[PDB]
Amino acid sequence: SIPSYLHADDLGPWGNYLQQVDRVAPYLGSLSRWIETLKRPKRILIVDVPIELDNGTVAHFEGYRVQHNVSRGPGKGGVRYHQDVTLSEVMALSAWMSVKNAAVNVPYGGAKGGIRVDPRKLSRGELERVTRRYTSEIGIIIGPNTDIPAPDVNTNEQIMAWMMDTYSMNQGQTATGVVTGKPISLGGSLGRKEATGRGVFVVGCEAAKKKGVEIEGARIAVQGFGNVGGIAAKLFQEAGAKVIAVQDHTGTIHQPAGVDTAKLLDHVGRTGGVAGFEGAEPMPNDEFWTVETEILIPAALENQITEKNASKIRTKIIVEGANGPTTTAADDILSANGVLVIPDVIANAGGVTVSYFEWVQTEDEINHRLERVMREAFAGVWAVAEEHKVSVRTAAFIVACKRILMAREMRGLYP
Amino acid sequence: SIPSYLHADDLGPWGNYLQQVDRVAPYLGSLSRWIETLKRPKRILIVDVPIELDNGTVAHFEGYRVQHNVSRGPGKGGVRYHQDVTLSEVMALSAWMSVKNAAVNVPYGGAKGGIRVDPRKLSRGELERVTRRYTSEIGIIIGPNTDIPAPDVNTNEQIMAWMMDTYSMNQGQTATGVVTGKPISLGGSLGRKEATGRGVFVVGCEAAKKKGVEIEGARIAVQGFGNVGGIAAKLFQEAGAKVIAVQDHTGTIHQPAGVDTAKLLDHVGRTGGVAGFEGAEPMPNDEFWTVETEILIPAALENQITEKNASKIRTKIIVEGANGPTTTAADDILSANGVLVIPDVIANAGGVTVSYFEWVQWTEDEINHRLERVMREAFAGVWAVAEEHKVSVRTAAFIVACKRILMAREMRGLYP
Amino acid sequence: SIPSYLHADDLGPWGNYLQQVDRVAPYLGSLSRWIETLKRPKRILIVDVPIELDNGTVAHFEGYRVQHNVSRGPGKGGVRYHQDVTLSEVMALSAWMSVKNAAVNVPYGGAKGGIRVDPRKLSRGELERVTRRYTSEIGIIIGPNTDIPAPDVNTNEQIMAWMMDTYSMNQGQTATGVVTGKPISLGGSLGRKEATGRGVFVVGCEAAKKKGVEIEGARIAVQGFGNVGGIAAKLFQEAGAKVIAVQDHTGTIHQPAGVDTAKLLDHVGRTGGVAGFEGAEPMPNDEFWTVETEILIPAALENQITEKNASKIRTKIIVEGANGPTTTAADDILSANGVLVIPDVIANAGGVTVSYFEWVQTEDEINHRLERVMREAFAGVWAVAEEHKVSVRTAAFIVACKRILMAREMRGLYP
Amino acid sequence: SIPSYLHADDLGPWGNYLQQVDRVAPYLGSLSRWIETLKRPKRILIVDVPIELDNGTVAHFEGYRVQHNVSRGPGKGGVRYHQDVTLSEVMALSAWMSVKNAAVNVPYGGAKGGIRVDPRKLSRGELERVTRRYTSEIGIIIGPNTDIPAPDVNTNEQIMAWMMDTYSMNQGQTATGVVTGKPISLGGSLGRKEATGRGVFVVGCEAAKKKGVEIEGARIAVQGFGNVGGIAAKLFQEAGAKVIAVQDHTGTIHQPAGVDTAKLLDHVGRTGGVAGFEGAEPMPNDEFWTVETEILIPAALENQITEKNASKIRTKIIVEGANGPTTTAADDILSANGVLVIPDVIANAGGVTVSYFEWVQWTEDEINHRLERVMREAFAGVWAVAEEHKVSVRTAAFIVACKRILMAREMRGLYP
Ligand SMILES: NC(=O)c1ccc[n+]([C@@H]2O[C@H](COP(=O)([O-])OP(=O)(O)OC[C@H]3O[C@@H](n4cnc5c(N)ncnc54)[C@H](O)[C@@H]3O)[C@@H](O)[C@H]2O)c1
Ligand SMILES: NC(=O)c1ccc[n+]([C@@H]2O[C@H](COP(=O)([O-])OP(=O)(O)OC[C@H]3O[C@@H](n4cnc5c(N)ncnc54)[C@H](O)[C@@H]3O)[C@@H](O)[C@H]2O)c1
Ligand SMILES: NC(=O)c1ccc[n+]([C@@H]2O[C@H](COP(=O)([O-])OP(=O)(O)OC[C@H]3O[C@@H](n4cnc5c(N)ncnc54)[C@H](O)[C@@H]3O)[C@@H](O)[C@H]2O)c1
Ligand SMILES: NC(=O)c1ccc[n+]([C@@H]2O[C@H](COP(=O)([O-])OP(=O)(O)OC[C@H]3O[C@@H](n4cnc5c(N)ncnc54)[C@H](O)[C@@H]3O)[C@@H](O)[C@H]2O)c1
Ligand SMILES: O=C(O)CCC(=O)C(=O)O
Ligand SMILES: O=C(O)CCC(=O)C(=O)O
Ligand SMILES: O=C(O)CCC(=O)C(=O)O
Ligand SMILES: O=C(O)CCC(=O)C(=O)O
């Protein structure tokens, strides 16, 4: 049964997560007794985030920090700034953290934050004030040893610096370990910046090996061209693939010869989106999903590959950079159509893997260890998929949830 | 706008509270720029409360602690165990705490807790385990100097004792100030246990003087016969009133000679409700609202006097012991019909008043004498404001309370 | 069943305390279920207290803090420095604290401290160093809101000042509420210094009314002439009584005319004890107990009125200033001889009552409220004794233990 | 002088420890002035552990946590559940932790915990409640940076999980570092679980080299077949040795061909002990000590090799898996009989060594490979000391450890 604070016909991403839980249920053996633990976050914190606007009036924004499961260790997970941030969305994101963390076996529980705001509508000062007030409000449950935030959509090294500074001033001492994804002047690295994109690239290459797809001249489509999508695209072109189609919030472009990802990155950084890129042609947004490719990389927001457009997708491999881009109804259609789907909770875990590295701590040393971690987790999940004759997503959930509920099992209930 | 985590077609009591806020808006003056602070709780904590049931299976209950506003001091407010506990309801209850605390001028912010559970369905052990797990889950935001819980619907000295012990054991030291409503053996009193009901009685008498109603012979109806309703009814009969009708969750009883509250209290204690009481007749639940009285006392749950039944009410004074029992639509109808309505946020504040006396530390009589006097003073103050602005006592109570709460916000400012 | 860390043949005062608990068991009713709580201290802390001696060598002393029961509130109770301090003794003293605190109804659990040292064998420097090391070592379980020490045998305002300072310096801030019995300069009072003796005097007068003993001309004998004994004798002489026999660790003196208590106080202060006092005749220690009196006040150490000498006693009232001066075998003998015995756990509760007054914070007003509390506590216990046909001691335990165990019952067990 | 809270005629294991300290006294040099530090634990905490039994009765158990010496670092040491747990035993166990941690040079002081309880007499629910109440009571002095418990007799990864969870719920955050010996799901390893038994095997092979004893074909007798005894016997059989006699609390078995340790471990798991094992013959308990072996491994409880049975032992090497299994009087007898005794404070330090590894953040084989190396090197260092002073390995081990502990005490000094 769903919690009374949610509406059953308005479950958003959390409704998808719950479907993914139902699908792993038959594979949990005696851990089944504990399955409801997956459907109930330990801690939901909803905080008022009031600031004085530049125009003189007071503005109130919804801030969230959800700790979904911390059986295995302190909470870990990013912070989203987006106009569509909601309780149900932050809950789902915190759950996929719990599952991805268990799946790649980092000693972290899952947590997530969000502010319901479009940062484009705020001045730089307003953005800073919102960030600091939010960090003050959630300070009561975060900390280097308790719950460690990180970037997500519309947040970045600057937002993390403001968070780290605010928490430090509040507490009275510099605490670099309270957030990851920090600027290098404060402890972070170019390693962490490209970690998520690089993980996506690595597991996409491992899947291509399985699917018999050659990376040289492989057609790639990417949704999103920010921290995850932009980096994944850069690495695939550098591997000799052709990134032939990109869609973001500003529109869609198309380049049969493959875009110059370097120039497109600079263009995205200069205008805020791919629309207007000189080295490509504009394309209707719907046509993006029908462009024939070898690999499709959803790396924008959730619920993008759905019952509605899944059948018209013509690709060999989907590699989920985004959290929850694909629904379970879509999974079924894509499988029936012979598409290999590499799940978010495996594919995008590069970020939290290096976040772990940053929390504990060449650039090549880091990356080579990450690539090892990502291949090994992929290898393991693949073996579980083969063993139980299930999709890679289900297999990922088998591995992650067995680790989560065994922790619950051993820890027990008090009292 | 309303927060995105609520639905507009499902606001519960929070919707009623927002309407009450709209009505104080014209009276805030320069503090109007802060009015949205009243519509946004500072802190919403929702916790999982898992236990193993006696039967071997794991059960998960919804737990809540909402700190609506702490501009003026630490959080203060009860914990409700009820099957219809929801986010919006605990939100509304915590907001009424902020207002009532500012109205009677105790240095507490408003907070409230809830567990979505029917205690009737739980064994005594299960109820303990639920209470302890809840307490350990919200431990991170409560404490004797931070947020202090107390009883509410279906909770009592035993539930409070369990919360206090749990918190103490988690913290590693006895912390008797972490909750109020404690049993005598842990720092509480019979004073606090009858405080809210006594506050209702005192305030109802002050109102009766204003409307020219004599207490001796006066007909009283009471919805709810628990901690608040039972004591209120008991005190009114002892003052010479006739409690002629009682409704609770088990049924409605009617007795024009006035019930023996001593015997009815005992009956509710043995059986669980007023249903089946010897000294009365059973009456249809809807009919309860139509019984002619001098004073009607809703002391059960919220949203009980509505546009559906407000025109049918025949009484001179409503004194709200319950939180949120009357909607703003009902207010308009009752006022049109010349009914005097004394708002919850004044009438039921006797509890948090003596809760303050428990937390901060004189005979019981002396303690009651100060309580009675505190309630009289706050009533007279709110009444003076009602006359000043020619508004209802509810609006005046909000004028007084929100001016205190928002001036605190104004002075504290925003950081950064 | 006694704990394994004690020896049955070597129980010391704990053995007497256990017999007292057995004597209250028939009167607990439904609270009998919890009676073992009285028999088991929540917390025993034994600490090494090493210092460097003046002679250049290292000395190790035994330090103790026992928290017997904290159901009703934070621990409260004094610290004894004495060569015969032992685990069993500190346990017993902490348990009498719990009981007296509930009998007089202050919101404190029972606790006690001790250092097995004879201060007469230490220089002032050494005594200070021992006091400070001991405070640092037990720091982890004491504090203004947790456990509040106080004086007892061979400790006083100077020991308390050192304890308070050490704790403040360890914690980084002045914390005056960490102990009671402080010097005036640090928050304390003459009211607290005389509180225990005054309580003994008050209660003694209430018993005298019950037994028809006139204070005017009454013969008083006091064992111990320290903080408790000295002050009680002083108040009784001021009330017109004759203090005719005093015994302390240095000897016994006798003065049928009644000693000048003021001069004897001065003499003890200068020489260390009553021995050699000019205004009295020396007398064998054993003969002390046979001197006929109206009121006998044991205000020294425990186990002083026993099966061996109880039959020899010729007095009308015994008022216990000391903790546990009278064994249960002695109670029975005394009972049979028509001697009224007013128990320690009522008679000496003046200290903790004004200690409470100190912990929360005129002198005449402060004493006027000490006297009212003591009379009301005495009348209440007297009522219970008559109601149940039991001794005053048993009645005091009835009142105290019903309050202690009802707090236990209500708090329950977690888990 | 012994502390007044102990009896000279009832010192238990603590008395044996003191004899051991006396034997190292001539070798301390200038650090002699601090010898009494070895004989006085910094901190003894004894706690009441009340629970409600399944039959409705309140039961009180004795809980202990003794922090013997923390000059060199945070406290580290196991928790024993046993019916003969006593103050003197937990003191002795804490002190051997101090010594072994210094001997193998891990940055931990010595501590130990226990509950005087026979787990066989409690249900699983009762055992859990005891564990949790104990953890909440000793919480005030344990923590990941303060004092980190671990397994010992009758405790294990399930007990560790419960301690960890309790401490985390009390503190309000997951704290996986508060204990070691955790299950894999909570951060523990198979390396840690086999660690002590493995270190016993490693040093046993290091002594076998010194004595020219071939592991292949060597006769082994083990007392105790739990976490230490079981894994040690397995590792020896896998190295070609024959495990010919096993004694545990249920009895003694004999098998001159060498037991299948895999099948015996399974039997012990299923029935609780070695009694009834089909693959061997029953044998009188006292005869266990007279069986001729190459290697004898006491891996049960203390005081098993004494004046009484020492002259009867026919073996080449004794390797102490247990804490304090051998008295000083037995030591002398064994030395005169040419038996080589490898002491507990070196031989069983494998656990704390990997406990350190767990607490701090390589495959399971690299973990083991590092364990093997540190154990060989610590053995070789103590051996060099023993030959330097012409003393036993036990005395040499104390020389190494006590010099390090007392130098730490010397530098830190006394405050004030
Ligand atoms: N370390 C990380 O940053 C990390 C780790 C794991 C998963 N993720 C997930 O990866 C995804 C992207 O994260 P980011 O860090 O790249 O965000 P980012 O803010 O750098 O860029 C976000 C991208 O999403 C696109 N987008 C937004 N709304 C869109 C719409 N309606 N239609 C199409 N595209 C739209 C934007 O145009 C932009 O390209 C999110 O799902 C995030 O949760 C991020
Ligand atoms: N100190 C306090 O307990 C306190 C303080 C201030 C306000 N209040 C308010 O007073 C009211 C009652 O508090 P309590 O402490 O009396 O609770 P209580 O649990 O002692 O009893 C509650 C009463 O409500 C009645 N009730 C429940 N459902 C009903 C229904 N559907 N129809 C009619 N009656 C119904 C129950 O039968 C019972 O008589 C609540 O609104 C509570 O918020 C209580
Ligand atoms: N606030 C308090 O100080 C307080 C409160 C309650 C109870 N008590 C009890 O009162 C008693 C005395 O307390 P104090 O504070 O007066 O101690 P104190 O150290 O001021 O004087 C103690 C007295 O005991 C005497 N004494 C010691 N050994 C003796 C022996 N073998 N024979 C005879 N006399 C001996 C000493 O000579 C001295 O007169 C103790 O039992 C203490 O626990 C003290
Ligand atoms: N990591 C560890 O577990 C660890 C580390 C270092 C030292 N030790 C020591 O090793 C010994 C056991 O460790 P464990 O972890 O194996 O305990 P365990 O509880 O797994 O098994 C204990 C063994 O002792 C046996 N035993 C109990 N009483 C006995 C008796 N009277 N006669 C003969 N055998 C008896 C039991 O039958 C069982 O075989 C203890 O001395 C413990 O302190 C354990
Ligand atoms: O780096 C992290 O902590 C994880 C970032 C995140 O939220 C994600 O993996 O989606
Ligand atoms: O006494 C308190 O602190 C809270 C009482 C309460 O919950 C209420 O006033 O409704
Ligand atoms: O003042 C106190 O806290 C108690 C003094 C004391 O030790 C006693 O009452 O015996
Ligand atoms: O793992 C540890 O901390 C040590 C276990 C223990 O108590 C021992 O070595 O005997």
Image: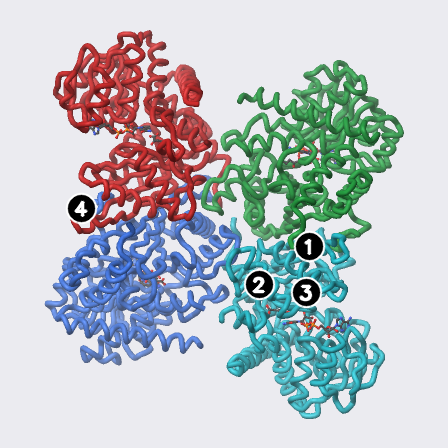
Chain colours: A cyan, B green, C red, D blue
Question: Tag on residue A49?
Answer: 1
Q: State the CA–CA distance, disc 1 to disc 2.
A: 17 Å
Q: Is mark 2 within 8 Å of ligand 5?
A: no
Q: Are marks 1 and 4 in contact (CB under 8 Å)?
A: no
Looking at the image, residue B77 lies above or below residue B228: below
Q: Is the residue marked by circle 1 packed among few (<14), some (14-19), or many (20+) residues within 10 Å?
A: many
- Quadrant location of residue B214? top right
Looking at the image, residue B63 lies above or below residue B307: below
User: In the displayed image of the protein, which residue is found farthest to the left?
Assistant: D336
Q: State the CA–CA distance, disc 3 to disc 4.
A: 69 Å
Question: Tag on residue A80?
Answer: 3
Left/right placement of residue D331 relative to residue C102 reads left
C280, A34: nearer the viewer: C280
Q: The residue tagged with tag 4: helix, strand or loop?
A: helix
D159, B293: nearer the viewer: B293
Amino acid type assigned to the residue bearing label 4 in the image: Asp
Dot 1 falls on which chain? A
- Residue to which mark 2 is pinned: A164
Q: State the CA–CA distance, disc 2 to disc 3.
A: 16 Å
**First in sequence: mark 2 vs mark 3:** 3
B294, B362: nearer the viewer: B362
Left/right placement of residue B39 relative to residue D126 reads right
Q: Are marks 3 and 4 on the same chain?
A: no
